Length: 20
Length: 429
Ligand SMILES: O=C(O)CNC(=O)C(=O)O
Ligand SMILES: [Mn+2]
Image (cartoon, rainbow over all chains, first blue to last red; front, top):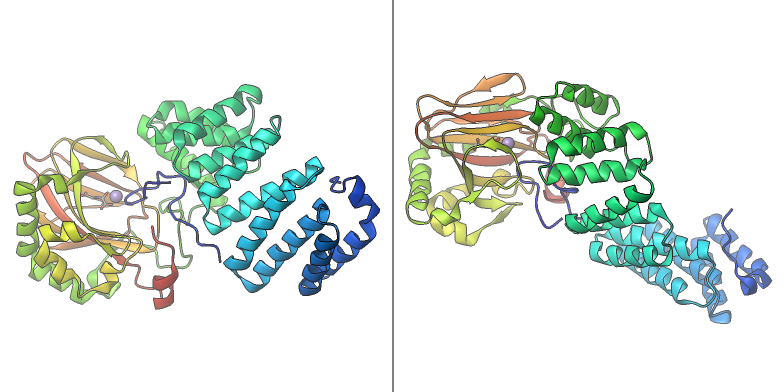
């Protein structure tokens, strides 16, 4: 999402996935 | 019943069924070999190639192997590269490709697959909706918004498009406009709309406009399992962690950290003030749309458990002091930062993303009146050289109505009940 959820929950997703 | 066999594949349906039988019986190794034999024998067969891919997929799940899954992602593309692929098979193969790319975190790759899907199937609204998600996952809100506008222009009652369009509007600070889309989308009951993100932001938007029905949606999001409670609305949680808005140092167990912060507070203060005075550009304005009004900026030393080396040049003794406490420097779901707030500031009620951190605030320059913070139902003030500790996954709200600036130091720690392996493995936020 090229922006991070620091103080809030404003991005569509807050993590980057790594599979298993 | 999908039509997965072209003309030629119908003539070898027996062989194809036998291999698929091995796969569904769970004999995945035999299935892989059987479909590999069918692919070498019938190199143009789309059903044989899809079987190979599905076998690799199943193997990847069995072995929990990302490497095997990358293999499967390539075979799903091979399927679509063959001649005379039935439409239902082409769609299944490329959809699963995109889904597994997203599962692995290959969001740009997933996006390209989804763009191809929408080209190949221009009348499939659901594929357009999935494309919009692709754009959202790479941070391309402008293109996502166009996709959902197209979807709504053809199917105006599509709930999935409604909630995602409302999410986008809300993220653009189009608060009033977002509310009908979020609300109608959740009420649609359509697949994909019963999602915590949309309850969270519908309630937040209503709170911002003064609409008192906000907590109705918080209660329903709680009842539907999206929120731990109506007060604690984080969406990236480890279930089971002790939940209370305010913590003491001993309750947290981080007594050495709190003591170090309080005993050395003037040094921490003075490094922050020096950065204010001669490197003010290190303080960046708050950029998550959290303010109603006012001026608020932060100077970040750590984020996602990574030291900002240039930043620490500005607060070198403070950074040295903190290196002794991995419970904060290694908190990959929190930050370490100075926070300056000026008069006339009001931060809207809001929730952090995760219940996995606790937030310490060390008072550094606190005007005697005008500054306060509410968490859940308890409201407190800061004091110079004293630490307050709250769980920002609970709704909290901040005011600054002094006549001069208010400087604090924010130190996130791992929730104390998280185990070492959890601290090592949880995805960073
Ligand atoms: O008041 C500040 O500077 C920061 N306050 C918060 O809302 C928080 O730390 O989450
Ligand atoms: Mn906050």
